Length: 51
Length: 50
Length: 405
Image (tube, rainbow over all chains, first blue to last red; front, side, top):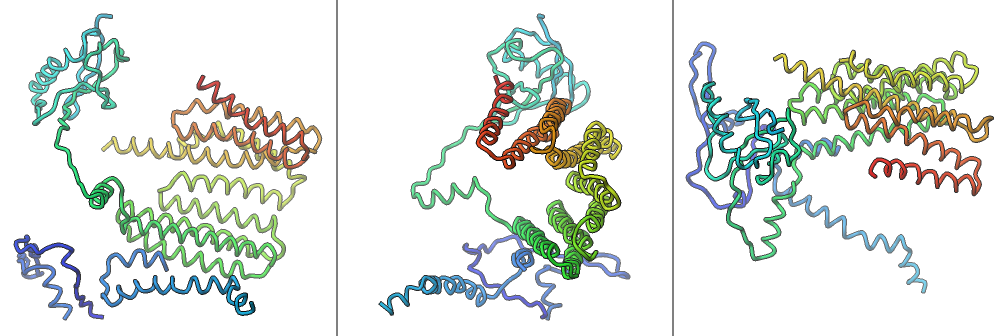
């Protein structure tokens, strides 16, 4: 019900790539704190809310 | 029901225990065909009352 | 005759009028020709044409096909006032690829030339199956009303109409792309059929003229309403409105008072005969500055195509009903059908559109075949069928032979 999902797959049918381009960090804003700031990868931000 | 399943399945993640179960439905569908067809053809009675 | 004037197209779109030597071979002119277009582009202040890697400069038709480098400009079918395009064509030379193991070889090759299934197409398949499913549902419910006067047909069909229309509304508002719109249109269009029979089935007693008035009426209204708020799929909705409208007129007259069906059929035939001449005018009135003209042109083109189809459907049903192998001067409607077909067969040449011209031409052919079939089923005897078979094969053979030979 909370939407936690557990990925299990055969590594996309390929070997690992340690040097892959990391995920782009997301920008956020606040009404009073109108100046935008970035907090981190979109994939990781969901976990803090799903829990 | 098929139109909904066709649009919904491609974007969801399913557990391996379920993906392993749908595979076995095909086999459970084949196993009864020959025994049922010969019954509809009335072969068993023709042999028993030889 | 020593020279010809033609418009030559160059990079990104400049057209230049030039007077070319009519008999020198084209390969002798492409180099100095390129210099001149560059000189004019340079003075105009635009970016000149330039080469990129390996390739060659070529002179082609506006269709892109290059002219034979050794032939004279007069030797080719290029006349004064025509236009050409100067172009750079890249080199295609590269190494060949080989795969030895037939298993891996077949997989790799076969995966390139053909398209595999994807989630986008998967939805259009399901959407089409549900549309087929409900048109079958209304068929069995309609067949029941033909033997029973109870409310079941309207009660059950009404809820289907509501359910199908409800789902279509969400898809229409959520849609984002042409693929998304296709699925929505197919679903909405599928709602017209159940709603239509749902209304016509409501009036009690045996089915006939009184029910006919409700059915073709709601049908015409629904098709028009969908066309008004959607503004897409013009041709198909237009066809439903026309056949629905004329059928409602016939239904109402027969329901109120009519001396004979022949009178109504004769009235409809005459209405359709005059409508063919009005169709282009109707189509024309039914329809950054560049956008408005192209939109107007394609919208107009669409309306005439649909409008012609609606008329074609009505005449064949009426015409085949008017002719008869036993009633009076059996030959009179046969020749009248012939004269009616002759107009359509000849007039098809007046329109530039391929599908419009093809539908007009086909409309005449089908009537002749349908009339002979009617006269073969009834008044059945070896002479009747023998004559009809010979006619039907000779009919188109002579037409194609006269055009191709």
